[PDB]
Image: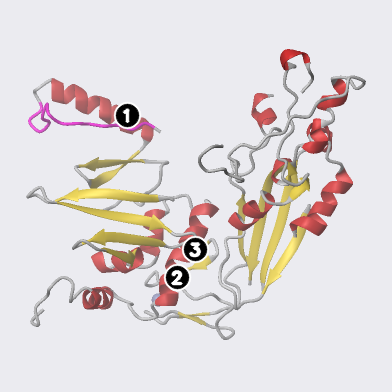
Amino acid sequence: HYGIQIRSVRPDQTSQTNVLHYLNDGQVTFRFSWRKNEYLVPVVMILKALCHTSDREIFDGIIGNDVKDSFLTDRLELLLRGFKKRYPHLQNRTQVLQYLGDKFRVVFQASPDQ
Amino acid sequence: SHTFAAGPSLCCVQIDGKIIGWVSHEQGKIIADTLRYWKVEGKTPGLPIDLEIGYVPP
Amino acid sequence: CEFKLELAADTEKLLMVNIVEEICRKSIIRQIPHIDRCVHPEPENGKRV
Amino acid sequence: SVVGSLIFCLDCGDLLENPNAVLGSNVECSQCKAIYPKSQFSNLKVVTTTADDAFPSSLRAKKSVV
Amino acid sequence: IVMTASAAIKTPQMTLPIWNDVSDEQADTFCKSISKVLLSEVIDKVIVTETTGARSYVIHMRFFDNNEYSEEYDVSKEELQNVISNQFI
Ligand SMILES: [Zn+2]
């Protein structure tokens, strides 16, 4: 029943919600809506797509100096290893981002040129 | 860009939905009491009176 | 009370604290079935209740 | 590069594999492919006390009052 | 009552008339034997210790004092050991 929700607005005052859900397995799920149906993405696919990351920088950006907090470390164990388990590929930014563009190619009405 | 910080032990300073930086809770109230004294006193050329500075204390 | 608990290396990480909490809330010490609490209120209208 | 139950690479920060699902004496990264010796990373120990709100009772209420 | 006729009633109760021979001290020491006691209601804190490199979990569960839970719930020391042995594990 837990989750977070932002309502981002564009500079032309157009809105777009982005919901993160918490699964009881230990992983989290990005959620959005482009047309009138929803889509569910794991967020490490989106964390590795936004910029050129390390994998400790995902750890060092959620965890502060509270390395000894064993709640936060163990729930983040499942989040990072779960992405390596499901996706043995998708290793740098230009390869995660082609997978994310391949699934949403037909729904974002992309050209045959893109 | 040079902070290495997260969590509620610090307080995150955000302007319109982006992170500007990180500062302590004790200094984060002092620079939330300072920015209200500087937007009401209209001598500062960057702080509008129409600004909303919502400080959430720990 | 302290007991060891061993697993192999094929198994990936279990939380094992959300497991123990959700089993400690289900394991009963002394339960009469379908009864959760027994209260002695003040005696209303003479009779003991 | 050993924090909690997980370990990272010293050169690209990538999350290394579990050191008991890999063949012995060597743990290899997947981006730098920097082979780390499986012998003595550490003894991977993590202690986790319960949430202190997890077990509500009539007797826990006597702790903070008295 | 009227509309759903629920056998899964939201708050079931039961009223038990006390005999006039037994007194009020023999009643509130009797309701402790009926009211349920969870294993959650006896534990102060639990500390796991996961060691790997064979996944070894050291489940150390810390209770209240025996002068503290055997007075509130009247749970004895030997009854608490069998719930761990035969009911919890
Ligand atoms: Zn590497």
Instruction: Specify the segment rendered in magenta.
Output: B44-57
The reply to whether discs 2 and 3 touch (Cβ–Cβ < 8 Å) is yes
Q: What element carries label 1?
A: helix
Q: Residue, x 32% and y 61% (percent of image)?
A: A30
**Chain for disc number 3:** A
Figure quadrant of residue B38: top left
Disc 1 marks which residue?
B29
State which quadrant residue A23 falls in.
bottom left
Say if D13 sits above or below D60 in the image: below
What residue sits right under mark 3 in the picture? A25
The answer to the question of whether label 1 and label 3 lie on touching residues, with beta carbons closer than 8 A, is no
SS at mark 3 in the image: loop
Image: E17 above or below E8: above
Let me know if residue D28 is in the magenta part: no
Q: Position of residue A40 (x, y in %)?
A: 32, 65
Residue E41, image x and y in percent? 71, 41
Which of the two marks, 2 or 3, is nearer to us in this view?
3
Sequence order check, earlier mark of 2 and 3:
3
**Chain assignment, label 1:** B
